[PDB]
Image (cartoon, coloured by chain):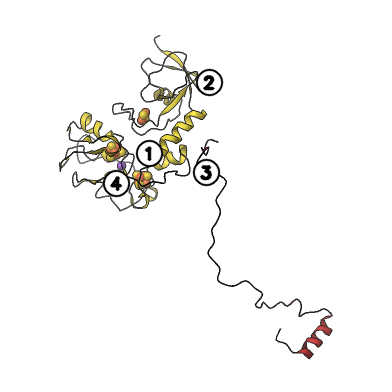
Chain colours: A red, B yellow
Amino acid sequence: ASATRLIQGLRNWASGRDLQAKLQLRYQEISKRTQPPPKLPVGPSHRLSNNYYCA
Amino acid sequence: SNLIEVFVDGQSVMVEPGTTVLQACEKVGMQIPRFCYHERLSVAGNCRMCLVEIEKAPKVVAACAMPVMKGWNILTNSEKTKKAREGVMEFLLANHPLDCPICDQGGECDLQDQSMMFGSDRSRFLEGKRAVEDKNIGPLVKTIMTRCIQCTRCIRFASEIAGVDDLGTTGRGNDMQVGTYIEKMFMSELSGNIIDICPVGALTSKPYAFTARPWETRKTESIDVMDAVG
Ligand code: SF4
Ligand code: SF4
Ligand code: FES
Ligand SMILES: [K+]
């Protein structure tokens, strides 16, 4: 992504495909390494009524 | 022949008169869950775990204290028997303290085993549990009364086999504690056997306390040589 325009032109001519639009080196488009804390949902049997184990 | 025939799960069996439901169910090779019944102690009938259903009878009977009669059919795997077992397990685990990692009964606990086998998988008790003051009854039996379930095998063992008559049940309601009401040092020739008959970790062996765990112990049978009883 930091490659120069003549190197990009030679690279695109030699490959035959546009390589800058699909770069294999990861950049700032990735998700951040820190996240807000999550709150997980509960299962279908997290109930206080008609939750007998024999059913 | 005075013996009568009863039915368990649609199967006939021949039992003696005066034989309870639990003895017949053990005769057909099944184990009804229990906390207070003992084959060497008197019947108390208070833990209510042994509740089963006789067919054509809309009330569960206690299998540890109900004599059988001719023509009775006993359903030990019906829906209401499992509902009663789950309810009794939930009531027992309502006030039980979260002490399983620091309790010597872990790995050989009756309460944990039958909670896995017959109880539910979650607790609906959102309130605060009770707390019972501890007691000091000697240098052999480590006592933590918070984990007791009031099964009263202490009382029957102390009053029938040891015959010391020191243990008792003080107080009324949920605040009733199994103790001696005073700083009484319970010492006898058969004291440590109460550690055998406690289904919970309320009474533990003081020298053995916090030393090992039953799942990593190899069992080797042997004979006692300290006394000539063998
Ligand atoms: S006696 Fe109570 S604390 Fe100890 S292992 Fe059993 S359930 Fe857990
Ligand atoms: S301390 Fe153990 S044996 Fe004694 S009454 Fe309580 S549960 Fe039963
Ligand atoms: S085993 Fe029958 S009530 Fe406890
Ligand atoms: K015990």
Helix, strand or loop at mark 2: loop
Q: Earlier in the sequence, mark 1 or mark 4?
A: 1
Q: Is residue A22 above or below residue B179?
A: below
Q: Position of residue A4 (x, y in %)?
A: 74, 90
Q: Position of residue B151 (x, y in %)?
A: 31, 35
Which span is picked out in magenta?
A: A28-52
What kind of residue is marked 3? Answer: Arg
Kindly identify which chain the residue marked by label 2 belongs to.
B
Kindly identify which chain the residue marked by label 1 belongs to.
B
Label 2 crowd bin: few (<14), some (14–19), many (20+), radius 10 Å: few
What kind of residue is marked 2? Answer: Gly
Q: Which residue is labeled 3 in the image?
A: A47
Is residue B191 in the magenta section? no
Label 3 crowd bin: few (<14), some (14–19), many (20+), radius 10 Å: few
Q: Is mark 2 within 8 Å of ligand 3?
A: no
- Residue B131: image tag: 4
Q: Which residue is labeled 1 in the image?
A: B92
Q: Disc 2 and disc 4: Cα gap in Å? A: 45 Å
Screen quadrant of the C terminus of chain B: top left
Q: Is residue B212 above or below residue B177?
A: below
